[PDB]
RNA sequence: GGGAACUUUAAGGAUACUGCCAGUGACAAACUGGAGGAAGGCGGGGACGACGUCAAGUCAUCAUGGCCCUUACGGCCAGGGCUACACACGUGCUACAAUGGUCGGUACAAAGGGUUGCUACACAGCGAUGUGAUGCUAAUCUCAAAAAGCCGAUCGUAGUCCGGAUUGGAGUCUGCAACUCGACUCCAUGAAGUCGGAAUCGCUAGUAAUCGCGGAUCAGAAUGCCGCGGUGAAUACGUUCCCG
């Protein structure tokens, strides 16, 4: 019943999808069964920034930043599975959390 | 037996249509308990009334999101799709009635510098 | 901003850092119900006897590059003038122009 | 009927009629009626004498007209004599609780005075 | 619009009698989107009229509307068929307001019943409009 | 106003001066900038020079002043009409 | 327990092109109508601002040529002011009521925020709130009650059971500290106002109107600003007149 839960967070959904694909392929190689990847709801934060130095309240830039989240479940681990996951390299821009 | 999905202004309706004798239930409630204003009930009942078939089917309906008008419209759309999924030849009559179309109108966003989607603050030359 | 105002902000931050633990202990003693009312009054007097800059309500957020005191955006630590320029040339990760 | 020295309307409910006495609001009226035992929807016209004196006894327990007006006047006069900030505002007939006076002070000031 | 001709919007018939006249009258009655209140008022008025006399509401209403319908607006300009119904329902709405019955549905029912016999504030509205119509 | 569970607020130096005078019986005014200190019953019978922004105004404390702040008796703005 | 159907979540794809039919146009561009289709002629909205104009705005975000001050035009502190008040204007909010006010019962959202934070629940208080205590680093727990809506009772056109300014008294919370100069709660008070002159503003559809909800700034302090959904209209014959 040793279940491994992996949560991926990023600011770039292509990067996060690449990482999720790499992880699921690495696990399927060692032969443990996988569940996911499951996409969690995205968070969106918006900002309004005045562009003129002194006075134009109607002249503004609207920016945003998104946080993408992916969930991966590992069931029936093989001994090689955890070692392969730990030897997996850390891609820049993607945050990975592993819970047992 | 047959299934239909309806959508109208952020409302979504799941409709299960079978053969029987006219029971109707929405979110484990009757039509009169669920909808208080009678025009919503007429909107819900329009498809079967237009077919003269209100005593030959059982309807099991779940609905979520939106307001009363949106939910009534979604339920009507779902009933139409469920009837079409039961008898294909019925579609011309429902399309003539106008029940097959998915209404796409939705709330417009507020815009920078305006009070609303279109309303503009009061202007003065002097 | 002038250099004096920036140094003033630095001095207040240093004072707040220096008096952090004593103030928290005093407030805990004040909010403690088991202690005698004489003890609570004494703690109130000691708290009122600290230097003014020890209190955090006198700190003002300023831009990390220019020291501007208006338009702060806690998330980035930059005022609007520098935030616009830094975002629009790509040095802020994940931030893009927003449309919806 | 005459209660506390004024004639309250007889064709209204008691909770609305008792509010016509200075110093009694809706909350106090329903409190008095609940304390005595009359329903809030009973009109004054269908109230017998005994319940009328029962209401009068309860109204005797709160400052209503002359005592209350005298007390308010004394409070204002004390501030004006003392000469604190609120007393100065009362003397000059200006807002007392910190509102703006550059515009929008017409309730205290009265109608506009032409230059 | 300096080049275009914009087609007149088409509104749905009412769910109860399937009458576009009733639907447009309801839209004229409604204020700020309270269609439920407007429906209650209009349906109550028609029900009251039907109780007073056993006549079918759709032709009852359209007959009274034809009687109140003006041929000339207010200084005579000439108007189109839609304008006829427009100002007819406009005047019909106002008279019930200054009537004195307790509920708006009852007030409107009284106004319709009295206009059906020519004794309606909308009726003298039309009469005055006509009296200025023979002016020019 | 200030919550009763905390009690009145008086500046420590002003309280020290007042209690010193009252333990003694001195009569010259007590000069202060503490416009925010509350008037306590011990203040009665004393003259306090309260700052008002540009000057020190003398205030002779009476019984009814108890419960006010010192600044209420030293106005800060000057107005005489338009 | 279980299922992977449905809703949803979120990545990748398909689809619309006058493609088909009937007339027009000119023998074209284009224009008119019909079928199928979720959608038909640019389906709706956003970002994107050509060559140029106004010695337009910003030396107080910042940088910078020149000029000026140097025991002071630099620097440190406490108190006060930016909140004044015979008046005039701009932008808003709340009303003048019955398509409404109050009371009781009962339904339906979207988006967003939360670890020096949001708090289930119990107790205390009329209430703002306080004490104990539980979950949450969040599609997991929480802010949170949507409001207008529907059913019933009452009020019966009154300056009122409309309106909620101003003032007296008593409190809570943040904060070293609410006098000048905070927000909120309770009792009392109950102003103008009965739809607004000459004149003038916004809007062509999920729009106007109306109803509630969230966030940045922020110890505390929105009727402003930026967003979200609910209910949901009327009218356009035309280019003389006004403006660009």
Image (tube, coloured by chain):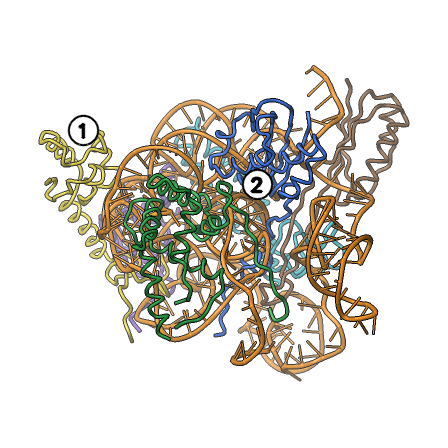
The label number, if any, that marks residue D36 in the structure image: 1
Estimate the x, y position of residue G101 in percent, counting from the top left. 34, 44
Q: Name the element at disc 2.
A: helix
Vertical arrangement, residue C14 with respect to residue G9, above or below: below
Colour chain F appears in = purple
Residue B119 is situated, as x and y percent measured from the top left of the image, at 54, 59
Total labels: the figure holds 2
Q: Where residue B40 is drawn, which disc sits there?
A: none
Q: Colour of chain E?
A: green
- Residue G54, position as x, y percentages in the image: 63, 81
Residue C55 visible in rendering: no
In the rendered structure, the colour chosen for chain D is yellow
Supply the letter of whichever chain is cyan: C
Q: Chain A is drawn in which colour?
A: brown
Pick whichever, C20 or F79, lies toward us: F79
Per the image, the residue denoted by label 2 is: B70
Q: What residue appears at the point 29 percent right and 71 percent down from the top-left corner?
A: F81
**In the rendered image, which quarter contains the N terminus of chain B?**
top right
Q: Identify which residue, C72 or F20, lies in the foreground.
A: C72
Q: Mark 2 lies on which chain?
A: B
Q: Residue at x 9, y 29 (%)?
A: D50
| Chain letter, blue | B
Q: Which of G202 and G172 lies nearest the eye of the viewer? A: G202
């Amino acid at each position: 019943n040793q279940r491994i839960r992996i949560r991926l967070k990023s600011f770039d959904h292509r990067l996060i999808d690449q990482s999720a694909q790499e992880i699921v392929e690495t696990a399927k190689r060692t032969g443990a069964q996988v569940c996911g990847p499951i996409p969690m709801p995205t968070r969106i934060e918006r900002f309004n920034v005045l562009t003129s130095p002194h006075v134009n309240k109607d002249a503004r830039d609207q920016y945003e930043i998104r946080t993408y989240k992916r969930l991966i479940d590992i069931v029936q681990p093989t001994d090689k599975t955890v070692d392969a996951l730990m030897k997996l390299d850390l891609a820049a821009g993607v945050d990975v959390q592993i819970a047992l | 037996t047959n299934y239909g999905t309806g959508r109208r202004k952020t409302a979504t309706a799941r409709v299960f249509l079978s053969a029987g004798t006219g029971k109707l239930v929405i979110n484990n409630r009757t039509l009169e308990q669920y909808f208080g204003r009678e025009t919503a009930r007429m909107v819900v009942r329009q498809p079967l009334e237009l077919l003269e078939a209100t005593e030959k089917y059982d309807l099991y309906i779940t609905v979520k999101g939106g307001g009363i008008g949106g939910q009534a419209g979604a339920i009507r759309h779902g009933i139409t799709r469920a009837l079409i999924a039961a008898d294909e030849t019925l579609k011309p009559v429902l399309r003539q009635a106008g029940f097959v179309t998915r209404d796409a109108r939705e709330v417009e966003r507020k815009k920078l510098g305006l009070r609303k989607a279109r309303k503009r603050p009061q202007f003065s030359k002097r | 901003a002038k250099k004096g105002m920036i140094n003033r902000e630095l001095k207040r931050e240093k004072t707040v850092a220096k008096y952090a633990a004593k103030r928290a202990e005093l407030k805990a003693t004040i909010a403690n119900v088991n202690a005698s009312d004489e003890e609570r009054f004494e703690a109130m007097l000691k708290l009122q006897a600290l230097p003014r800059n020890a209190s955090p309500v006198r700190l003002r957020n300023r831009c990390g590059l220019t020291g501007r005191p208006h338009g702060y955006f806690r998330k980035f630590g930059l005022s609007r003038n520098k935030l616009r320029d830094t975002v629009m040339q790509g040095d802020v990760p994940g931030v893009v122009k927003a449309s919806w | 009927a005459r209660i506390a020295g004024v004639n309250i309307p007889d064709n209204k409910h008691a909770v609305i009629s008792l509010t016509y006495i200075f110093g009694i609001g809706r909350h106090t009226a329903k409190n008095i009626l609940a304390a005595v035992g009359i329903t809030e929807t009973t009109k004054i016209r269908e109230l017998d004498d005994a319940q009328l004196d029962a209401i009068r006894a309860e109204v005797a327990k709160v400052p209503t007209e002359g005592d209350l007006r005298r007390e308010i006047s004394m409070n204002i006069k004390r501030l004006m004599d003392l000469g604190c900030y609120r007393g100065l505002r009362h003397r000059r007939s200006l807002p007392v609780r910190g509102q703006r006076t550059k515009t929008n002070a017409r309730t205290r000031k009265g109608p506009r005075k032409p230059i | 619009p300096r080049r275009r001709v914009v087609a007149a919007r088409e509104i749905l018939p009412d769910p109860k009698f399937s009458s576009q006249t009733i639907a447009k009258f309801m839209n004229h009655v409604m204020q700020d989107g309270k269609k439920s209140i407007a429906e209650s008022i209009v349906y109550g008025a028609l029900e009251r009229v039907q109780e007073k006399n056993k006549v079918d509401p759709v032709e009852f209403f359209e007959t009274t509307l034809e009687k109140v319908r003006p041929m000339v607006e207010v200084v005579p300009m000439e108007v189109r068929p839609s304008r006829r119904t427009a100002l007819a329902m406009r005047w019909l709405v106002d008279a019930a307001a200054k009537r004195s019955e307790k509920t708006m549905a009852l007030r409107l029912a009284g106004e319709l019943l009295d206009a059906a016999e020519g004794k309606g504030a909308a009726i003298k509205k039309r009469e005055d409009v006509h009296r200025m119509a023979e002016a020019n | 106003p200030r919550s009763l569970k905390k009690g009145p607020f008086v500046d420590a130096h002003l309280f020290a001066k007042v209690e010193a005078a009252v333990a003694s019986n001195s009569r010259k005014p007590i000069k202060t900038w503490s416009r925010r200190s509350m008037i306590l019953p011990d203040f009665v019978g004393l003259t306090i020079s309260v700052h008002n922004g540009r000057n020190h105004v003398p205030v002779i404390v009476t019984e009814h002043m108890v419960g006010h702040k010192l600044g209420e008796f030293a106005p800060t703005r000057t107005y005489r009409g338009h």
